Length: 69
Length: 70
Image (cartoon, helix red, strand yellow):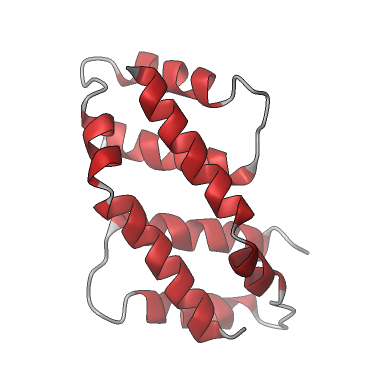
């Protein structure tokens, strides 16, 4: 427990997002014609179990960022 | 197709929320000044020089839990 430990945990997590080549490839393999359709399709499957927890929403926000930027 | 990605993202989000160590350290921020905590953690996260989007999203995950507790 400390501010150092928290920063390293977040640093580790963020670095896991960007360096996960499998995720990056799946994200690139989706589409680039019409992001709106891709977003709602991915969102529907992510939440088909009904669980709308904050971690998943942030994952979806990361995905949308890569789609529009 | 879209399924493997959605499953991948769902797993990442559930892992964030089940990171008990992470949830526990974040819950310990009973500070008079959230701003200082925010800048302190953000400074350590970027002390190398790499301002990559993944770290920013994790900082955004942290900041949301930090600020939306009041």
